[PDB]
Length: 130
Image (cartoon, rainbow, N blue to C red; front, side, top):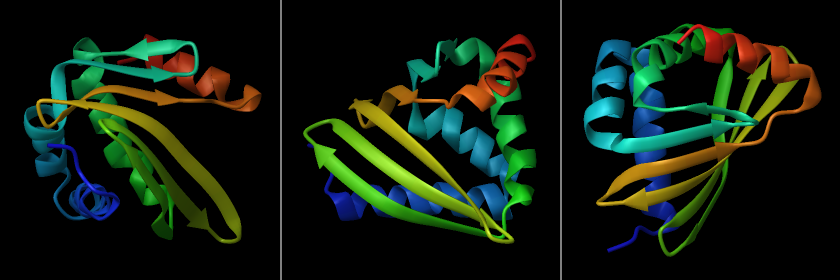
């Protein structure tokens, strides 16, 4: 049973809400409900997995306060392959967080994000420090 665009949007919105309102629940839910034990998160050339998740999810909790507005701009489903684009804004600056996801057993098994050239050092530091 795969999910519709609307069902995916509802899940994404709830996790965003948790990130802002109860970040400790965000982290517990992300690791217990949302992400598969074997999850692989491929951010550019850098792979994050369960070994990284405690510190990776903490980093998301802190990064979230950087933005004034967060909105889902695109959800596209194709069987168990999902694409989500989220727009993040702060004072006229706009970032686009775009991810491709594979779902197994109702959980995320793979996440893939591309990274532009000026963000590689950020991701490398995260990989060496989660």
